[PDB]
Amino acid sequence: LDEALMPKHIALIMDGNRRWAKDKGLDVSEGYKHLFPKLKEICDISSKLGIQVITAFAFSTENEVDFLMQMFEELYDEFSRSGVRVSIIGCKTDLPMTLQKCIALTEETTKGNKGLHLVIALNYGGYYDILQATKSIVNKAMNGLLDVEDINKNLFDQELESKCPNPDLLIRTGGDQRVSNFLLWQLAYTEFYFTKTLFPDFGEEDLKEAIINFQQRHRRFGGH
Amino acid sequence: LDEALMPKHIALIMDGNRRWAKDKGLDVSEGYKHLFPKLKEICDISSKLGIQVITAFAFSTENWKRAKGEVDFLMQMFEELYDEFSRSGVRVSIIGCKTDLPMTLQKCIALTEETTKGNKGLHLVIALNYGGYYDILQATKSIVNKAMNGLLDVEDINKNLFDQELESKCPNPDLLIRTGGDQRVSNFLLWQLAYTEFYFTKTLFPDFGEEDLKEAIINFQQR
Ligand SMILES: CC(C)CCOP(=O)(O)OP(=O)(O)O
Ligand SMILES: CC(C)CCOP(=O)(O)OP(=O)(O)O
Ligand SMILES: CC(C)CCOP(=O)(O)OP(=O)(O)O
Ligand SMILES: [Mg+2]
Image (spheres, rainbow over the protein chains, first blue to last red):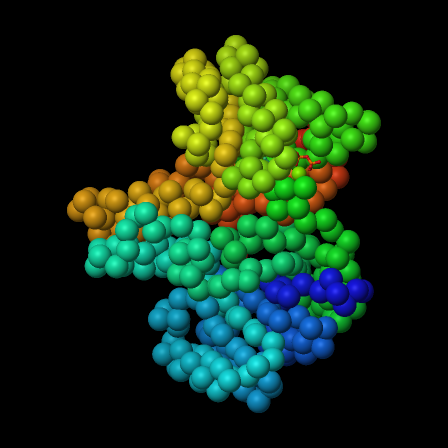
């Protein structure tokens, strides 16, 4: 592990919680109860390593489920007094009104934090991020606030919910090799790391192993 | 393992050509020269398997950053499109910003598209001066133009409409194969790859063969 070659932004697809529980013969709720505690541990480790941002896929727009929407309220107690600045991205208006308030509370109470920035993607999809940006651009163009000529990569970077700097590394647990409608635009040149390890079993040595693998890779960005 | 039930659409990042050449103590041009013959070979195999679409990444919007000599060689070599695919039985389309390519390449592309448009087998989409950012931006511009001319409302902007404004269309790739060992999509079909299964192989593109293709397809199937 070389401290100089640390990625600044890690994206995380936190897959395998359901399978973890079912394979163990536990109630599926037991898998979900590991989600935020494990994410908090990963934030703690990452922050020590000098990682600046984590964007973590918690619930896609395509994803029982009454349980999940209630559990997602315990963001507050994990993070509110934690030193982590927390942002939530996704379709917030589709959520039960009380989860909406819990999310806002978590965001408001941590917005002053100067440590690691945790971005939780909850009812999020890449398609929907791109579409909301497109709509924002169209409304602006309709109101004479920009021209088609102004529609470029940087404009789009500013209208998307997940902002620059983009992820350097994406880690997906659970064994499947796909992005599953996570950060599509933002992943254009991200290094991908896939592991069979299920999210509840993913520890500090697994995280370190992913980062070491990242550091060995040559990033060329269309050049060299 | 292999069930005779196949992906409709494979996306292909044709990578590792320069390293292939330099491993053999050759000029990079020699690596590039295998690009289209290899692509044509992959189309033949895939067609026998019953694959309907291949989208192959030939030149990105970022590849302009390379040495002027290499970019010049590539832009010249790409004119061999017509000789390579005219009589191949493949229906060929190009996606990407055609208007910024040399005029001779543009007319060569148009001719290759025109001459193969009646082919009823495999559809080969070649991404040339293409990027995912580019695709999404041109789609967005088109939607903005239509909204400003009263041809649609902001409430009509949904996944289904966007699917139809993008250059790479439905069905989206079932499987992405990238040669050369690097584990990234490098600004290829970003929107279109949202649920695609990724297969990354260390095998360099000029060495890619029928066994490497069947291995990828097994992974897709095991899913
Ligand atoms: C758990 C998570 C949001 C990451 C994967 O979400 P998903 O299971 O819906 O994606 P897939 O169905 O494609 O595997
Ligand atoms: C194959 C292609 C036309 C573009 C993708 O390959 P690339 O070598 O430009 O991608 P990287 O620089 O990210 O390795
Ligand atoms: C087809 C193309 C121009 C890009 C893929 O080949 P490449 O030049 O990137 O080969 P290398 O990865 O070895 O540099
Ligand atoms: Mg390359």
